[PDB]
Image: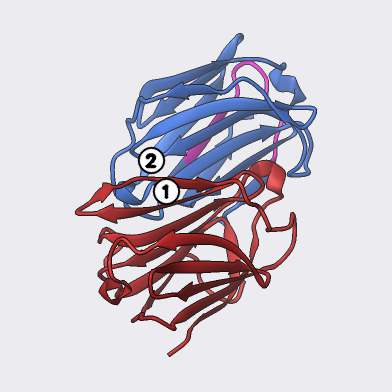
Chain colours: A red, B blue
């Protein structure tokens, strides 16, 4: 809808930064749409990813990093606070030791920093969603 | 680009029908964009799927059916004729006993009919691609 998808925005992050996203899946959960949010070290899409957050709606979440072009140790969660057919509000906050992922106001996932968040230069939001809000607290 | 994505078109299929698609992934293969083509029994996206063809570009292809709302036995192929960053031409032909998937003019995947192709009423093409051509031979 309102924002282009894939959505790419330059960004700087440190402890206390929050990335807030509002959007809606493009398909019912039965069709397993995805959402992905990638925290990149450079503006190019092929650059390393300090934190990749990938939702398969109704099924699972996987998180990982891509370092020197290589995907690293995948982490999986079956927590699924997202609601079929509904708009969601997603908040990713930078804590001292990890990212905190809030969904609709509830803590839902965490991911320990593998690389300092100060390495981030770009955030990309893509896959099977419409996007109405993207904000980085500065 | 030219066609909306997700792209949904009513369709009737029988032996000798061909569905031809031209498109391009929205991201480099390192980012694992998807392409999916679903042959549905009704116009609604939640209806059963006689043949679901899902490409994870650079990684794998999985194929399945969704019958009475339940995904069935998944089939996987690591054949990857798609080229990183390039437009592709995909042809799905209905043979008497199976679907034949051509990629850029080469036979690449097959999938035996689990349900008669005459059950199809709709084709949907979606996930991380731009779409410039969609044609059903009639």
Magenta stretch, residue numbers: B10-21
Q: Any magenta on residue A36?
A: no
Residue A67, image quadrant: bottom left
In the image shown, does A20 or B106 lie closer to the viewer? A20
Q: Point out residue B130 in the picture as x, y percentages from the top left corner.
A: 46, 54
Is B12 colored magenta in this rendering?
Answer: yes
Q: Specify whether residue B95 is in view.
A: no
Report the residue that reaches farthest toward the bottom.
A138
Judging by the rendered image, the residue that carries numbered circle 2 is B57
Labels in figure, total: 2
| Front residue of A91 and A46 | A91
Question: Residue B33 got which mark?
Answer: 1
Image spot of residue B103 (x, y percent) = 39, 30
Query: Measuring 74% from the left and 54% from the top, which residue is drawn there?
Result: A84
Q: Disc 1 on helix, strand or loop?
A: loop
Q: Mark 2 lies on which chain?
A: B
Seen in the picture, residue A72 relative to B71 is either above or below; the reply is below
Q: In the image, is A92 to the left or to the right of B25?
A: right
x, y (%) of residue A34? 56, 51
Same-chain status of marks 1 and 2: yes
Residue B60 appears at what percent x and percent y? Answer: 40, 32
Sequence-first disc among 1 and 2: 1
Residue A73 vs residue A21, the one in the foreground: A73
Judging from the image, mark 1 belongs to the subunit labelled B
Task: Please report the residue visible at 76 percent of the width from the left and 31 percent of the height from the top.
Answer: B41
Q: Are marks 1 and 2 in contact (CB under 8 Å)?
A: yes
């Amino acid at each position: 809808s309102l924002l282009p998808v894939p959505y790419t925005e330059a960004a700087s992050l440190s402890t206390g930064s929050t990335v807030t996203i509002k959007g809606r899946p493009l398909a019912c959960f039965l069709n397993e749409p995805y959402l992905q949010v990638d925290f990149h070290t450079e503006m190019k899409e092929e650059s390393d990813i300090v934190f990749a957050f990938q939702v398969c709606f109704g099924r699972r979440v996987v998180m990982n990093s891509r370092e020197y072009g290589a995907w690293k140790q995948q982490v999986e969660s079956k927590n699924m606070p997202f609601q079929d057919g509904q708009e969601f509000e997603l908040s990713i906050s930078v804590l001292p030791d990890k990212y905190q992922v809030m969904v609709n106001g509830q803590s839902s996932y965490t991911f320990d920093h593998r690389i300092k968040p100060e390495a981030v230069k770009m955030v990309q939001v893509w896959r099977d969603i419409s996007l109405t809000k993207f904000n980085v607290s500065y």
